[PDB]
Amino acid sequence: STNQLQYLQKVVLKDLWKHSFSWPFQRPVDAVKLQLPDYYTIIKNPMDLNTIKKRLENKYYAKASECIEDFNTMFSNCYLYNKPGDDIVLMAQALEKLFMQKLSQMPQE
Amino acid sequence: STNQLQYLQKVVLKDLWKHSFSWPFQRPVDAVKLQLPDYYTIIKNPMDLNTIKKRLENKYYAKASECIEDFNTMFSNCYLYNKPGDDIVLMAQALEKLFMQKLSQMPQE
Ligand SMILES: CCS(=O)(=O)Nc1cccc(-c2cn(C)c(=O)c3ccccc23)c1
Ligand SMILES: CCS(=O)(=O)Nc1cccc(-c2cn(C)c(=O)c3ccccc23)c1
Image 1 (tube, chains in turn red, yellow):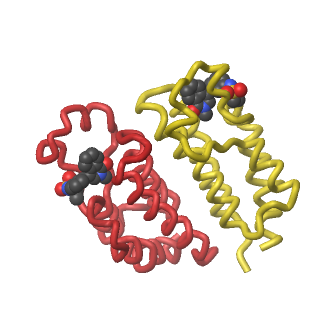
Image 2: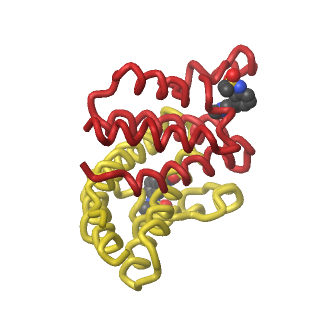
């Protein structure tokens, strides 16, 4: 599991962060700053790239599947809160496609 | 690759289909039957388990990544159209969890 978690930190997370569309995902959605009155009510488990980064650095995950769940939650949260056609959805879809590509190259340990 | 498309058909597709929550995804969303006046307007590429199945049967995909993209489109279509807390979303999330589990077991090279 440690080889895979290492790949998720040094390859997947790094490459997602470098992508030009990553900036809205680099910190938790700040619903007060953004004036989103229902966000915290209906998005039960907010997730973002910095929380995943900190969890990997602190060895919070026991298995790679736990970390992959958090990546997937960040994307579906975006899709669930927003609507088709929103530019934020376009950016999430670009990162999700890159995330999916890098997962395909994960060293099967 | 042929090994991976092969796994996607007899392993990933078969296990998603047998899941108790797969039935809303076994045919295209019929917006007239369900009286969803905006579905075909805002969901640009509808996708379902039967479309993927026939495409795999007909050798439509040239690479496993294109079939994986259709699976992801089916899930995000559902998240985009519906709202958090909807029961349809819970079943999509259960299938998408199973999808990522089978993906981690895909034979690499
Ligand atoms: C860096 C986190 S931030 O909250 O400090 N800045 C920031 C700036 C612009 C856009 C969003 C943003 C991100 N995501 C993922 C959303 O789903 C969303 C939904 C509605 C409105 C805005 C957003 C966040
Ligand atoms: C087998 C496809 S069906 O259209 O013949 N039957 C069917 C029956 C119940 C529910 C849905 C259904 C499925 N999905 C994926 C949705 O996103 C959705 C959104 C709003 C309302 C209903 C649905 C479809």
